[PDB]
Amino acid sequence: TLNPSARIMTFYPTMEEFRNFSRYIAYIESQGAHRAGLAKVVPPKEWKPRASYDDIDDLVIPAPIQQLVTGQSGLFTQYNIQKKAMTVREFRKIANSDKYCTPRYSEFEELERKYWKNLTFNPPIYGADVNGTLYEKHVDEWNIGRLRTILDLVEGVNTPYLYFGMWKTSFAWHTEDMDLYSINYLHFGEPKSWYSVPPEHGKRLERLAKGFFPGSAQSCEAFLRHKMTLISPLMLKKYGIPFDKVTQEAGEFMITFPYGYHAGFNHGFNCAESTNFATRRWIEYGKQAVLCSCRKDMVKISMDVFVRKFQPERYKLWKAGKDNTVIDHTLPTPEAAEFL
Ligand SMILES: O=c1[nH]cnc2c(-n3cc(CCN4CCC5(CCc6ccccc65)CC4)cn3)nccc12
Ligand SMILES: [Cl-]
Ligand SMILES: [Zn+2]
Ligand SMILES: [Zn+2]
Image (cartoon, rainbow, N blue to C red; front, side, top):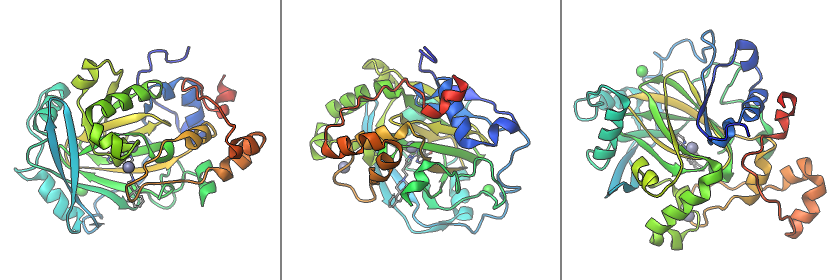
């Protein structure tokens, strides 16, 4: 009944609302935010995670990736080529050069058309998965480095990663590892555009992708976890896959929800910080997540600790294999009770 449209919702918390992260996640779920699989949270103007970003020029990007894209007719495969380490200074120079800078554009629709028309040409460099934070030590509100969710019970899923983008750099269709939530903050720079498929329609996307990449499907059941498959919004529209789009601007947060498929691209030189987190609602998703058998650096979490603590009644039944729980993607987290 809440957000029946499953459209991306935007939230504007006051400084008071913003102070308790986990409570605010529970609040947005009470509002139906989770149904779209992606939500935007604009922080109060007074909030800043770092005073300035002018001291990061010598920050090392250990493994930049040149993103080679192959395909046609809205279906593409992205291949990553690891390049040697570069500084933020060397990266920003390449990002803003004539070769790699953002093209001239009026409306977003124009930039998006240029993205889908040129993604296979002039492969850009993505300064992705840099272990680190740009948050100052004293920042207690929405600190990606120290979120303090139930995911902390596990103790690279709890650690922050930095992503230095340039025009046309992309993230392929995927859900988070272990079908967890994620938080993404755009520290500075040019926007980041996102596409999302509601969790309730996530199996329709997987079936479509399997139909298009049968070689990839037979090799690995969870082949989208490789984060190599790019599918244009027009292909999604053509095959009746429901989706929504949103542009994230500097100083805004994006939340991805369990089993929320998302993809997107960077408009130009930017920097985003990201991590995974959990709520009590996630435990069932973690228990039922279809994982990637083959690829290296694929995250796996032992669910045992979570079932023992939050589902003790179900522990023996689940470990036995008799746990037949069916996930209702429309239900908010149990923590959302105080708002319902
Ligand atoms: O703007 C974006 N850009 C890039 N990526 C995005 C994105 N996601 C990326 C992942 C995979 C992150 N994951 C971290 C741990 C790794 C880094 C290297 C390593 C080594 C061992 C184990 C794990 C890992 C693998 C990789 C998930 N979501 N979602 C939304 C937005 C973006
Ligand atoms: Cl800069
Ligand atoms: Zn993601
Ligand atoms: Zn695999």
